[PDB]
Length: 433
Ligand SMILES: *[C@H]1O[C@H](CO)[C@@H](O)[C@H](O)[C@@H]1O
Image 1: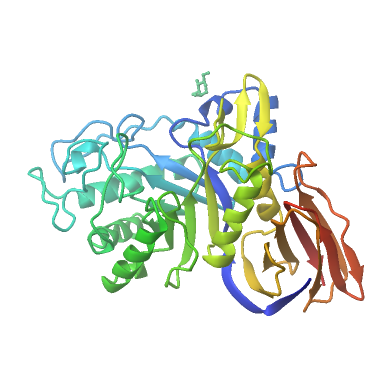
Image 2 (image 1 turned 135 degrees about the horizontal axis):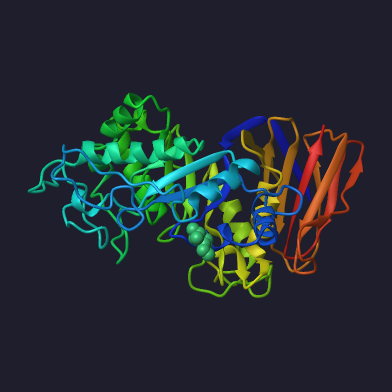
């Protein structure tokens, strides 16, 4: 029952929580009525009625929708760039994100253009020409690919949007039948990173490099150690991973902030369900996964796949079905973290979690202490928070009985915060000392 919270013991910095609007999935929303646009963007970004999300991940398209859809005559020949100021809805989405509280934009390529790769195709894998052990008859396209990624960044800068981070790979351990590009190791990745870093700096930009968005955490572990041995981590700003093939239950050995940059239930229907049977698309399942990432794997960020799309399955947090906008249970799992744990928060020490209650705590830059308690028991659990002396508490809960986060009746005795955590619920305490 007694949880100790220790703000003098701190761990990782929190960068935030977010999602993507890649592959044109958000473009019908970008083109919808002002009323639909407002409903969708408030669900994603509002800190009072939505999920308060703080990170947007955009895709850099490789062929169709690319800024360089047609090969030049060779790897050092003058490119022909295109720019429509739309980017399949991502310019609109980026401007909405900046207007409504997003702290970081990350632009991530799923592949280089086909003419820069060993397989001369945007899909079914292939390697960037000129990386270690990847010789192409047409030559070494490393500088061409760095120049291409910088032009995309400048295109966004010309629309007034500053990209914070750039990634040059997506799941490079995976070769599906759509935009993809591989690496054999972090050692091979290290043959391109210095070229990209130098090209960004030379263009007068400060964009940070993120790598390498593996399909699973086990490759993020392997590749980070290889990048460190190759001396490439000095050029990186973030280490990234997806959680599809494997999840994190331990932190990566790095001083860089680590982002979980894509994870979702891709298979199941969209559901408003918070808890029913522990299914993969349930809100409470996702509360526990975010908890695992932030508390067990020391993540600085946790991203879903798609924020909002039309006729969504579970791959999206919010759906647009005609003119009707609906929030998933998963959206409210994100909300119970993201509304309250703001960028530049630091995770802090807790001890004394009851059985099957997952606890985390955070200190915001403004000094608020956020304690999250996920009760996975089939019964209410009474807790007390010692180690902090509260002057005030605002608390919120989410369970099957409410349709969105609702005021929670916290106790406060002699500066000790407490409460009765409902069964199969999440409670967030925002404590002022
Ligand atoms: C949203 O949809 C409109 C047409 O309905 C497009 O013109 C726009 O670029 C966006 O895709």
